[PDB]
Length: 191
Length: 373
Image 1 (cartoon, one colour):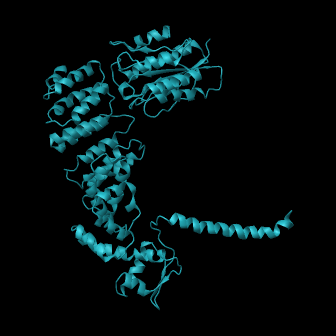
Image 2: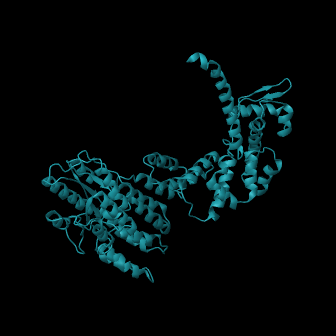
Image 3: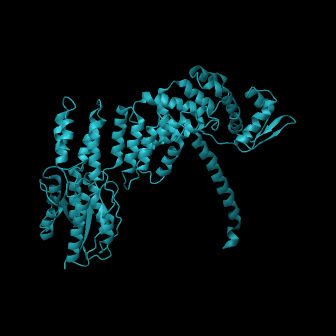
């Protein structure tokens, strides 16, 4: 199977507590963690997946482990109130990826951005060239309400990698009512 | 339910403009940009009959959404209570919001501070000290919010207004003086704020001087706006002691509340000079005479006993009194402030100790370095 370590990032920003995604984004992104942890389980047994809180202070409560049980426990009562912070959210998972015992696993990060961010374009392009030097491939899936047809995030994924690098894909929520399972139905079949 | 917020959609000219977006915020079912926009309308001064009607819909939001923090619910209820004018029905509804909301973040600190802010009309003294004591007990873990500690000062200051142990007000106002990071409020309020703070802190019996915290950098800009008779008399209580002109000048400046504590201030400066007379001299030479104390404190020779021995009970000096010549032998001292050009002379007193030990000790083992090998 493919060798890599996937680090899932839940969105704890205060804008993620609304029930627009049925029944609530808390359970919606919980099912999103359910489908990414079960797919990586069906993908390779050697994949270890932790969680990271992006907004406010960034702390990983569950050390990187192949078992998602403790991750599912932290999905409940997470108290996702705070202001979204982007620039640190990728690097905090990058440090968790440098603590891996085995060096044969590729560095992989999946994050959810459900809130408008104040991150400047200079900061995301500095992280883009930094990830170019660090080879890390990040697959982001945009939830929630944000700038219509997100650009700085799309340009972030574009300028993140190149040639090929097969790759970083960005999935933005369509402007219409839908279930969270329908939003994650596309990435699970094809990245 | 939609028509309930549609009848309240127009509060006046220009309101339905942004309300066209406000009603489009819950159609997308986002209650957060809705929270910030509604809270902005609640923060926007109004009649206000709009928030009183729509608070039931905001309550309906909190029902099925089950999430949104009570912080915003306290911020809206403090705006509505002003228009309700009745604290009792506000206490029944606020305590209802206290028991109906639970989150990982502690809601007891924000609810009890809201109850304490609404308890000013009860009027006071009955349940005040109990809930006020519960605020900082629940604030001990984990005080990372920094926002509610100012509300703790609000209910603690209104708890002090009964007078109320003046000595405690400086400690509570210290808590506020360190709680808020940036003042971000007009100095015209903080000039009298630090004024009555200087009054209640100086008139306190537990603190005889504390001239150190009088120089605190965040309050010194507030003292610059204040008249300089208070700052100069605070320097009289910093050093002094008499300085009979300045301790009278604070009676010229502040008429009330000084007449009761005036004799206490005189006793406080009479025990204040005892540390500074032995501290100022290079000395020691720590043995003084009755003529020094009786001339400085301008008190009779019979009361210098009570004078110096009370300072022994204060704890600023442990010294003993030689009553044959009526001399006073000081011991140790109470450190208070000091000053610029003192770090330099401190390096002189140090470097001299440096070359002393260096020379002599390098002479010691200079003799015996041979025999060691």
